[PDB]
Image 1 (cartoon, rainbow over the protein chains, first blue to last red):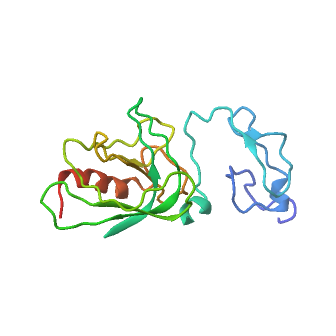
Image 2 (cartoon, helix red, strand yellow):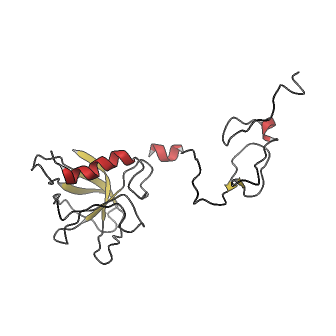
Image 3 (cartoon, rainbow over the protein chains, first blue to last red):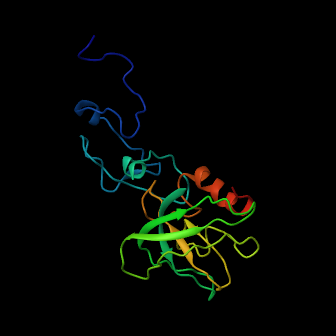
Amino acid sequence: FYKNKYSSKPYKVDNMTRILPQQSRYISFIKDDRFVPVRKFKGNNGVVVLRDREPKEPVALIETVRQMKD
Amino acid sequence: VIKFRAGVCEYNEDSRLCTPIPVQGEIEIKPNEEEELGFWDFEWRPTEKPVGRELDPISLILIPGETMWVPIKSSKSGRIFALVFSSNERYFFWLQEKNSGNLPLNELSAKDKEIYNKMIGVLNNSS
């Protein structure tokens, strides 16, 4: 099939990857975990900001081009 | 001859806080030939920001048993390179090495291994 399904549709998908308008609908942050939107997820593309419960605890990050190039 | 961004800094024996006066310039450190221990000429030069205090060129020698380094002396700033001379020619410097910005980062820069070799190395040996 193609329209209904195209096989094995749930995956765990990280922050800042190729995410399309279709795929963006189905995003749910777990609200039992640290990172959740300040408001609520907008269900479409663009920059979203997530409120962090505890910054003292380490978390894994990605470093920006701003730090690297100056 | 090894050169890096640095500002001049104000020292304290008052409680050993060492509050910077940020500036902009380059430190020029010369590898010399003088001795076989200590004796590295720390000459500081401004490039920009004449505001705050300024230090015209002064060579400062690495004096073993009077000069001690640590990067935090207060934890209000990091990237400090301290030349302790008991106020007989004392001046302090605040590195501003761009690799992560000119903002201070504690326990020196974010290119740890590269800055660390130098800092230990000036005390130990010479060219």
